[PDB]
């Protein structure tokens, strides 16, 4: 509360570390469904069904331009990528599988880097 603060967590490396994690996600062989925005002209249903589209290139631009106020807003956009994927794709599809693999991969790096 006022004039009563928890001890200061060092957050000065967060930007760089989120960038590294993102690089690793970008270079994973199963990243291909997620590298770019889904083409809303060419994929029936996507526009209406997925209220908040998200992809790695868009997270990368947001990161590079100071649009994440903190590391939690970054993790939210990453998880949004996988949550969207699960909404639109059967678990037993290449894309559905890619999304479960990438989420698992992300969550481990997240915990190992920050928790």
Image: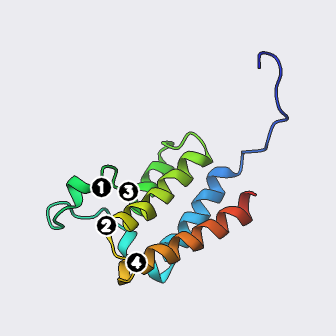
SS for dot 3 = loop
Q: Is residue 97 above or below residue 84?
A: below
Q: Quadrant of the C terminus?
A: bottom right
Which mark sits nearer the N-terminus, 3 or 4? Answer: 3
Q: Nearer the viewer, mark 3 or mark 4?
A: 4
Question: Dot 2: what SS?
Answer: helix
10 is higher (above) or lower (below) than 113: above
Q: Point out which mark residue 54 bears.
A: 3
Task: Tell me the residue that label 4 is attached to.
Answer: 91
Does residue 112 appear to the left or right of 102 in the view shown?
A: right
Lower sequence index among marks 1 and 2: 1
Q: Residues within 10 Å of mark 3 (few under 14, many from 20)?
A: many
Gap in angstroms between the C-alphas marked 3 and 1: 9 Å
First along the sequence among labels 2 and 3: 3
Residue matched to label 2:
88
Cβ–Cβ below 8 Å for labels 3 and 1? no
Q: Are marks 3 and 4 in contact (CB under 8 Å)?
A: no
């Amino acid at each position: 509360s006022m004039s009563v603060k928890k001890p200061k967590r060092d957050d000065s490396k967060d930007l760089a570390l989120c960038s590294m994690i993102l690089t690793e996600m970008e270079t994973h062989e199963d990243a291909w469904p997620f590298l770019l925005p889904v083409n809303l002209k060419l994929v029936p249903g996507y526009k209406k069904v997925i209220k908040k589209p998200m992809d790695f290139s868009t997270i990368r631009e947001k990161l590079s331009s100071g649009q994440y106020p903190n590391l939690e807003t970054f993790a939210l956009d990453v998880r949004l990528v996988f949550d969207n994927c699960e909404t639109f794709n059967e678990d037993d599809s290449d894309i559905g599988r890619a999304g479960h693999n990438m989420r698992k991969y992300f969550e481990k790096k997240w915990t190992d880097t920050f928790k």
